[PDB]
Amino acid sequence: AGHMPEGSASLQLAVGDRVVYPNQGVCRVSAIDVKEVAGQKLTFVTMRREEDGAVVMVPEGKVLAIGVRKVASAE
């Protein structure tokens, strides 16, 4: 059920783009901003799954550590 995270936009992820985790499931981007956490300044994306009403936030410049691929084409 539901449509998968397809690709039809630019390279870098934007607001309203689609995201999928390696196990968690699928979410939808709502807003994106940059901040300093634990002594580290980077772009932190904020997604909100309307399926249950949960929110997920991950580092766009540090996703390589989590192993999550969130992009207009990347899953």
Image: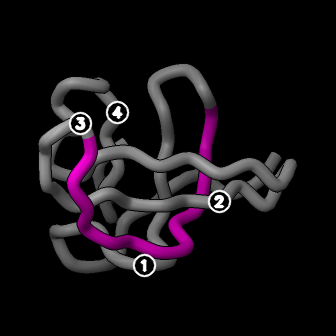
Q: Secondary structure at mark 1?
A: loop
Please identify the quarter of the rendering in which residue 53 is found: bottom right
Q: Which residues are magenta?
A: 25-37
Q: Is residue 32 above or below residue 2?
A: below
Which residue is depicted at the point 50% across and 42% down? 20
Left or right of residue 75, residue 55 in this image: right
Q: Which residue is mark 2?
A: 48
Q: Which is more foreground, mark 3 or mark 2? A: 3
Q: Which is more foreground, mark 1 or mark 3? A: 3
Q: Are marks 3 and 2 in contact (CB under 8 Å)?
A: no
Residue 29 covered by magenta stretch: yes
Q: Secondary structure at mark 4?
A: loop
Please identify the quarter of the rendering in which residue 69 is found: top left
Q: Which residue is mark 4?
A: 68
Q: Which residue is mark 3?
A: 38
Which residue is depicted at the point 55% across and 73% down? 30
Q: Are marks 1 and 2 in contact (CB under 8 Å)?
A: no
How are the residues colored?
Answer: one colour
Marks 1/4: CA–CA distance: 17 Å
Type of amino acid under label 4 = Val
Q: Which is more foreground, mark 2 or mark 4? A: 2
